[PDB]
Amino acid sequence: LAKRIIAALEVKDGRVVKGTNFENLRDSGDPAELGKFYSEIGIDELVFHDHTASVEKRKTMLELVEKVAEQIDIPFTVGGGIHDFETASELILRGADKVSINTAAVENPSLITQIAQTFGSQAVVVAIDAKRVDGEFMVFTYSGKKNTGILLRDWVVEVEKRGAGEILLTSIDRDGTKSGYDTEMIRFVRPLTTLPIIASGGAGKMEHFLEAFLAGADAALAASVFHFREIDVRELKEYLKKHGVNVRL
Picture 1 (cartoon, rainbow, N blue to C red):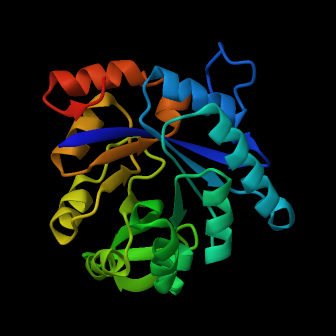
Picture 2 (picture 1 turned 90 degrees about the horizontal axis):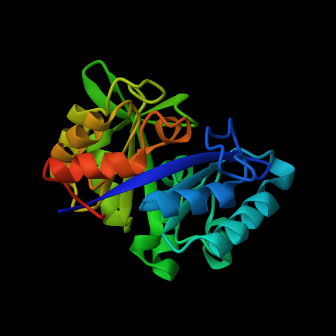
């Protein structure tokens, strides 16, 4: 099955947060320029997660989307504080291919269906942040601050029922570490859904990507390993292809 390598760019006020090690760029903090660069070195898709203050957030995210869309021809997803249909709609119309929803989806699962009814299931990425609590995988909202008491098992099934197109599955246990993707979590989710699963959290070395794909991920997302050039994207794809993973070269 075909596998995707996805770069996540954390943004705020139209700037990439903590930038990159790429000396070749005019501006290593320019999300559009960085996105273009990633598409040229072989990234399959981009995910932008915005952290801009409330007063300028809506306009800032729309400007980001417009600027990014001019520079790239590969799919991109935008998210971070999308709480209703109109916000999602404006972002897709302005150029995003997909939107990520998380806290708002948990609080109002019909939001998934609402977006999907106009933009198709393929436009809706449900980001699920999960962690082990007393031996069970639980869903967390508010940037991992709130244990919802909802079992990951139940939420995955509901997300697909509501019409999501893809699940962006972040293990809070691994996110920010470089210890590996949470392959147990990925394997737990795999049989519960037909949807593409984007593995997120824990990437540290090329072998972690192989492990994630063996676990049943359809895509693997990473940020700082790419931005700080711990992993070269071309080298990663060549590595994965060598070991039998169907990646696009």
